[PDB]
Image (spheres, coloured by chain):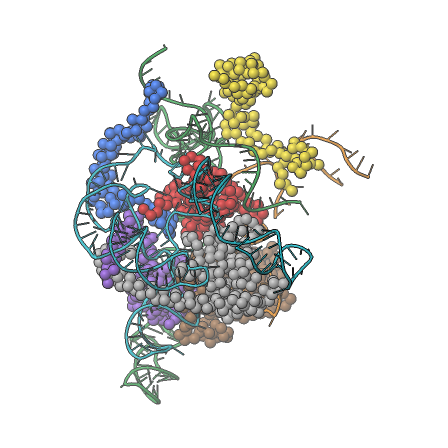
Chain colours: A yellow, B blue, D brown, E red, F purple, G cyan, H orange, I green
Amino acid sequence: PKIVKKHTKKFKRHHSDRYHRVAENWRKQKRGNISQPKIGYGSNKKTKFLSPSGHKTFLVANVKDLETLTMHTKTYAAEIAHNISAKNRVVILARAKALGIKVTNPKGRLALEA
Amino acid sequence: TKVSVEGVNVEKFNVEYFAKEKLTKKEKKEANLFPEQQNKEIKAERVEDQKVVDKALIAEIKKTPLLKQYLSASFSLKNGDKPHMLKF
Amino acid sequence: VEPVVVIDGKGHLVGRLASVVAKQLLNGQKIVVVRAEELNISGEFFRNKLKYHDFLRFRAPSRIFYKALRGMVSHKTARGKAALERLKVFEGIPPPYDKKKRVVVPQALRVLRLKPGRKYTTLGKLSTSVGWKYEDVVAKLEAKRKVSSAEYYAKKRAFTKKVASANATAAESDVAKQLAALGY
Amino acid sequence: AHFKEYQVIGRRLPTESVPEPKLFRMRIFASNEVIAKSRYWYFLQKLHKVKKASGEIVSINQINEAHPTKVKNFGVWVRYDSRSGTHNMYKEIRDVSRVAAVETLYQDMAARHRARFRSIHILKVAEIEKTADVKRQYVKQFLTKDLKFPLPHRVQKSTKTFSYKRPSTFY
Amino acid sequence: AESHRLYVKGKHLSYQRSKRVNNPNVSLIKIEGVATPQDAQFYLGKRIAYVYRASKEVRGSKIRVMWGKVTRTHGNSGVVRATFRNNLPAKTFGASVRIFLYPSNI
Amino acid sequence: NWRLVEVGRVVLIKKGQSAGKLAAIVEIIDQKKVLIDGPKAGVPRQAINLGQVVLTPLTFALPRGARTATVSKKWAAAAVCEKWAASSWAKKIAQRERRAALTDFERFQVMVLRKQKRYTVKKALAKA
RNA sequence: CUCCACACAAUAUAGAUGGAUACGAAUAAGGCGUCCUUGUGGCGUCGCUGAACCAUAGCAGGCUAGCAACGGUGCACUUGGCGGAAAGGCCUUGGGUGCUUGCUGGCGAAUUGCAAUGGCGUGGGGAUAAAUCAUUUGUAUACGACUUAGA
RNA sequence: UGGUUCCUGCCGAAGAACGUAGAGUUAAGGUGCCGGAAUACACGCUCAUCAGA
RNA sequence: UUUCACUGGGCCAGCAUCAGUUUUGGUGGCAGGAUAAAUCCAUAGGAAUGUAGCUUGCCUCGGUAAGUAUUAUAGCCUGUGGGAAUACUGCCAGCUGGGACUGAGGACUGCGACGUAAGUCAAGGAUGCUGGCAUAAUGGUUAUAUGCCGC
């Protein structure tokens, strides 16, 4: 469907630029030119957790995790975890293209030689 | 400004007549990776249709004064041309 | 509709013309305002003299009208500065603008806005009364300009009289009647 | 807004053993019927001790002009309140119709006397039929034989931005 | 021969605004030779292009175009509201913007 | 030479339901308002403010407070319809109406005939 | 001002895509034309908007054919005059050489497939009129500065 | 006395009650220019040698 | 494996037909009023900001004036009678046009309507057609600029 986002930017603390010690996470203060988080900005329940590709992401550590997305190919998309070694990433890619599952992050820690 | 369409037997060609053509054999493997550019020409049947319509249309035009030269000249908007006021 | 609009200042009001021009510069129309010394002010000379006085606690009429105009535009913005950069203001009509037509702004005309039987004020007399020592220089150039312009207009009227004669002898022709048929 | 004449009749209610009271009739100039009825009660209480609950309206009516083509002349009695004190005033009006004269009269009274539509209480509008009963000089100014004068305000709305003509009140 | 204009040029006046808050989404257009809203009814829904010239040559030309359309009238003077695909950079106030005749009713 | 507001001054209502119809001042109301009737043009007898109307330099004799049947009689006997049509100003008004009435092939014929007339005039020019 | 090296250029920046298209004054008055008694004369006209006027066909404007006129018009010249308020433009002579839609012809356009805009800087050398520093003077001078004079 | 460490939702005292947007219509307030929007219209009054808004 | 034929995803557009909200037009038929009033026509009186006529006086061979003179060589007003029309106000489950925003939902069920019938449909929320796109389409990031707001 047509994904509505309701808020493109981020929600930052008041005076977060004014000091380097102050973080940028949302912390409630305890003018109105600051966008404050609230439940009205909560996205549509169908559209929630959707990539710009239109899938829901799913972290995959190994091939047995990849096989759990066998039936739900058009709905989900596999994302390789950040700490997977490069021997296993090519096996995961070959298995996923065999399964026909869209990998969100191919070409991670990998190159194509000859 | 109006002309009579009645001299022309327009009905023959249809929406399907203007369907843009397709290729086969995956363009015959791009002639084995060598491109060729002879396909630019127009089919003669289109030209013949244009001539057949054009004769009976010019025969209508030549009865009216200055209409050939009107169709030959293009159109633009001059200074002060106000199309909401400009009755057409 | 015109790239550069040339506006005469004779017989006009200060603020209404300033409002019109200030609107058009923010609209992007390039404007030169000429014969600025002949701008007219509502009220008597003396009131307006006191107004320039208590303001003063630049003497040229162009500076005066520029002041009035600059007050209406938000001058501190970059957009207002570009709008002011579109503007030119001149007392008299220097070249090249002497050879071009000067439009008027009817909603800022003195003779239309003022009720008859009211005192007004000439801006050049005001500037000379407050220390702009150039008004006699102006009228001297303007007299020569009016001489040459009367020469130009006398030539122009004779040539257009010849054009009128040629259009008169062009009449009764069938192409003229076909223009009449089309309305011209 | 633009007013209207109204024949308004009130009859304050026939009580037990009092049948058919006297059907008091007035003529109200009002933009609608509703404020006409309100003004009718506002006069009827000033006539005598009625209330809108005490009586009722018989018939609300609009009445047109019989001859709205002829320019008639009018003598009008007005009473109103310069807030503390009241006083009457007699004005003479040259007008085609009655209700336009009453319109112009309200405009003039609000101009010269700062009086509202509620403060003004119309006593009488009647046509002055023959000439020289026009007591006022300014209406009599237009009673002359063969009257001619030029237009004032030759200034018109130019409707355009710039003029090439250097225009002139050429009249 | 001398002219090739199939549009009406008109000034990008401003954004829709109060005294303190301006809306960049709706833009305000002055169409030349239009003083009445009834004349502006002719210009409703019409396709608008802002033409400008860039330094770089994006696709065979250095000239780029924003598009959009007239939505509704604005005020008494025939000033016309407009909505574009991307909003205007607002340094284009008083700029000449092209208003095309398609979608033509006539 | 002045026009004057007066009885028998034929006028032209530039703004209103008429928006240009020949009428005549039958009677004056004041400096602001008058009584007019335009029964030949079709605008009825009515009171009007003078701003909505313009005076024409044409006039004729019209009785004071004359009724509409008498008005149309004196109108036709004045024959100022023809005197109006003979005026170059009404010719210009009809011309600017006809220019709005133009068609694009008509306007193209205007272009062509302007070319041909200009050719003939420039031959007539530069010989005299 | 001039010889090598390389970066755009044959463009545009507040907004090009028919033309900024020139009397002056008066307004309870003007203008134009005309006549005479040249006037504060008479007559007629006009305004009441530029909604005007001028330009405007041709591949974003092709290639040719004649008919007619001695027109129009571009460009480069050429002749002379006018323009100083910031003239930087205007007007003219004379040819040249284009186009000419004033008229009539004859071939080309497509498929872009139904809208998607579609000389100037650097870097390194060469040449030059002066200026400065230095010397010197004292009408000057806290110092600058001033100021002589010197191939 | 001063300080007292994450978020969101719900409940919550001693002209207009405001989730997030889109579109429309309006209250008040305005509509010479800044400044968006009639230098609208109509009728009267005021020329002030620092009216008045 | 080979021949031949057909077809292709996603996004962004434009158009058509719809639906929902809205805005702006054009146009028709009604119903009420004092059954509009008026106007127009018919009649009778009246008067003047008295038309024709007459008298008189100054005076450019005839202009004026001030009497007469109530229609004559203008007319007006009022009264009464006849006939509509239109204004205003309201209604239409009258017709028709333009523009904007929206496309939620997701086999069928329901209310309908048109249809003799079978079927269809604007009827329990949008579908159809076409275009562009891999040296993509397009989208994002920053720094600057613009405008508005911000102690």
Quadrant including the C terminus of chain E: top left
Which one is in front, A96 or G127? G127
Which one is in front, A47 or F17? A47
The residue lying at 41 percent from left, 73 percent from top is D147
The residue lying at 48 percent from left, 72 percent from top is D139
Q: Residue G5: x percent and y percent?
A: 46, 35
Which one is in front, B60 or F17? B60
Which one is in front, I40 or C147? C147
Image quarter of residue B16? top left
Q: Residue A65: x percent and y percent?
A: 57, 15
The residue lying at 59 percent from left, 31 percent from top is A42
Horizontal relation, residue F73 to residue G15: left or right? left
Horizontal relation, residue F49 to residue I43: left or right? right
Horizontal relation, residue F15 to residue C17: left or right? left
Residue F128 seen in render: yes
Q: Residue I72: x percent and y percent?
A: 29, 75
Residue F69 seen in render: no
The residue lying at 25 percent from left, 42 percent from top is B3
Q: Residue B40: x percent and y percent?
A: 30, 29
Please say if G111 is above or below F82: above
Please say if F101 is above or below C111: above
Total labels drawn: 0
